[PDB]
Image (tube, coloured by chain):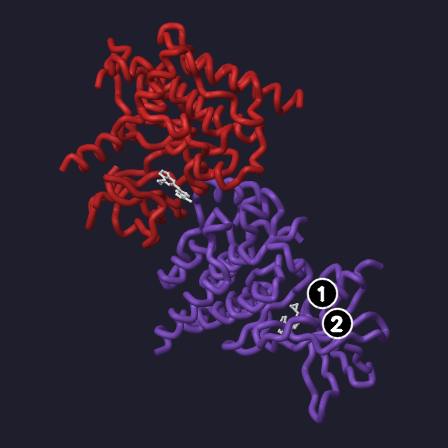
Chain colours: A red, B purple
Amino acid sequence: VYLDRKLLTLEDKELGSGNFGTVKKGYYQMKKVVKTVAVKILKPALKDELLAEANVMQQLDNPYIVRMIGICEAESWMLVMEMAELGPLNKYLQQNRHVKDKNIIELVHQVSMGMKYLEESNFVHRDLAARNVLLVTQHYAKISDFGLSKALRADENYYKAKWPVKWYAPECINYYKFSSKSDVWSFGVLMWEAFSYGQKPYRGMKGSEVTAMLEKGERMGCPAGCPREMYDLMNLCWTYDVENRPGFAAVELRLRNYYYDVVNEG
Amino acid sequence: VYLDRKLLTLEDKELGSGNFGTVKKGYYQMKKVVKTVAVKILKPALKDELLAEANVMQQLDNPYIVRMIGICEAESWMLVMEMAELGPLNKYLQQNRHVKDKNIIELVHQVSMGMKYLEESNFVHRDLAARNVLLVTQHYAKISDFGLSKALRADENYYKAKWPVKWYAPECINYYKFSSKSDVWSFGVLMWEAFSYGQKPYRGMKGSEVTAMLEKGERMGCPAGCPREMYDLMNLCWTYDVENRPGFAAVELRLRNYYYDVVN
Ligand SMILES: Cc1n[nH]c2cc(Nc3nc(NC4CC4)c4occc4n3)ccc12
Ligand SMILES: Cc1n[nH]c2cc(Nc3nc(NC4CC4)c4occc4n3)ccc12
């Protein structure tokens, strides 16, 4: 997967930014056509981190997960990925509030599908948020940003450790253990964010304030006009006890079963 | 607006046809000379359908837009326009592969100027394609077939709905929202055809196949010998998100500057 710089064509304008560098829009002269590509460009460990993300990606093959097109060594380092034409879900739901509840369920259910694959493949996302969910169409979501993501060992159930504490489960805070159940906590916080329309979780609260709230059995409320059955599920995602918290299999099922009704019985 | 049939002389051979009727070539006793005219002749609602086309035309005065001379209520209804001596760009370019890159740029830049006028006047062409661009000279093009064109209200940015999918933008296919931004998508499809020398876009594919190809982030490739910068510009037109897509002012500004350099 070492792409040819002659085929790649960049848009001299960014759609991303970060410690890594800039993410510019591009066009890659594919098999017979031209595929629009998102391209992470390195401005060290930044090259090891980008080779990590490139490895976590090359393995994962799922519709609801950003597919990678390949690496491209040229004037700089290029991580070539399948472009999500509409952008990050938090910034998209802020701008478009006419996005009906049904459209929102369909999108979070697509995240629960991609996450269920990540679970089955033995991968921890570790940064699963509204920001890191990008849109192909208004009705097609892909899970992005695999920089904190970790491939698990065959005999291992969890990983043991920058600090997205608002998306983090209590065992990540307290004991640094991350598993697919910790991503189920993040998914809860992500599900909240969408129904809120990109409103930031635990608005104004500091990291320890969030930790203290969750230890008191306190949770974020039901965003305005969110279907009760979705808030029901958020709190289920938000179970303090890791052993009793559902897996993505059971979460995606609850989203699938709800959606199946919603479209037909509504 | 109401032409004397005493001044209108019609030929036998047609320049086109449709459900509307025939497009006979004609001559019109004008000022002190004779103007060559293209005449749309009805074969019901089609009358108020062709009156809609005559109305869009009456309002538009720009060199790169097929001027209307007037109407004629004689044998059958006649819509009298200014003759495009060489005809449709696709057929012209299919039948002329000697036409150089500098020549095609100049013609698509001319389409882009007439389109910048139309955008500024708050009209949506809705049928922009190589076939609806007619050549007056191998160096003077005109936007025609204002059949699908609509005139937006002073407060609306778009229009909400024959259906040339292969030219339509995704927001049109999905939600039926035509605007000058949707005409930029079609403009990009026009720009492709012209460098393809009249080759039909997305050959063999059905409407849904095209739609699926677009959502997959795939676009038509670079036609053979097409200046890279003109291919870079098609992809700009071919922006999925309408908000991030260039307008006609932005499209003309890129063609004007390229051509400014290319000729000089
Ligand atoms: C309006 C707007 N802002 N940003 C955008 C980013 C995109 N598309 C996109 N962006 C990536 N990286 C960027 C940091 C997000 C991607 O990475 C993998 C796929 C992918 N697709 C589209 C629109 C916007
Ligand atoms: C060789 C050849 N074939 N067709 C031609 C059409 C023209 N000129 C023309 N044609 C119109 N309508 C035609 C259906 C396209 C026009 O409508 C308004 C103006 C106008 N000027 C010239 C040559 C040819």
Give the image quarter of residue B50.
bottom right
Residues at discs 1 and 2 both on one chain: yes
Q: Which chain letter matches label 2?
A: B
From the viewer's side, name the closer residue of A130 and B166.
Answer: A130
Kindly identify the residue that appears in the image at 49 percent across and 20 percent down: A221
Dot 2 amino acid type: Leu
> Which mark is on residue A5?
none
Which residue is disc 2 drawn over?
B79
Residue B129 showing in the rendered view:
yes
Q: Earlier in the sequence, mark 1 or mark 2?
A: 1
Q: Which chain letter matches label 1?
A: B
Q: Quadrant of ligand 1?
A: top left
Eye-nearest disc, 1 or 2:
1
Query: Label 2 near label 1: C-beta < 8 Å?
Result: yes
Kindly identify the residue that appears in the image at 51 percent across and 40 percent down: B212
Residue B248 rendering spot, x and y as whole percentages: 50, 63
Q: Quadrant of the N terminus of chain A?
A: top left
Secondary structure at numbered mark 2:
strand
Kindly identify the residue that appears in the image at 40 percent across and 12 percent down: A247
Total numbered labels placed on residues in the image:
2
Residue B152 rendering spot, x and y as whole percentages: 65, 58
Residue B221 versus residue A104 in the image, above or below: below
Lateral position of residue B25 relative to residue A25, left or right? right
Residue B252 versus residue B9 in the image, above or below: above
Which residue is disc 1 drawn over?
B53
Q: Quadrant of the C terminus of chain A?
A: top right
Residue A29 showing in the rendered view:
no
Dot 1 amino acid type: Glu
Name the residue furthest bottom. B32
From the viewer's side, name the closer residue of A247 and B40.
Answer: A247
